[PDB]
Length: 32
Image (tube, rainbow, N blue to C red; front, side, top):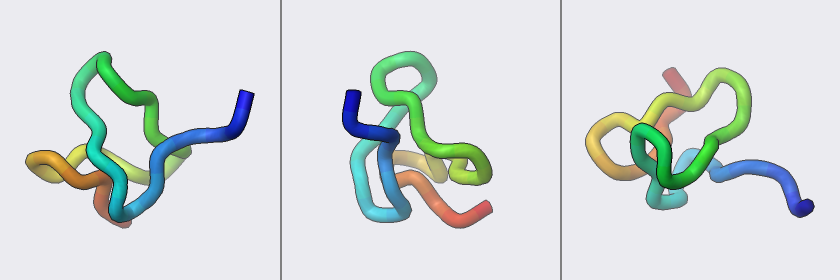
């Protein structure tokens, strides 16, 4: 239990849950 991805972490649709307000903009979570 650490937290969530950041605005520079690799995420996806259901592979890595990012924090609230960050959407996978292609591959790296972005600041919306």
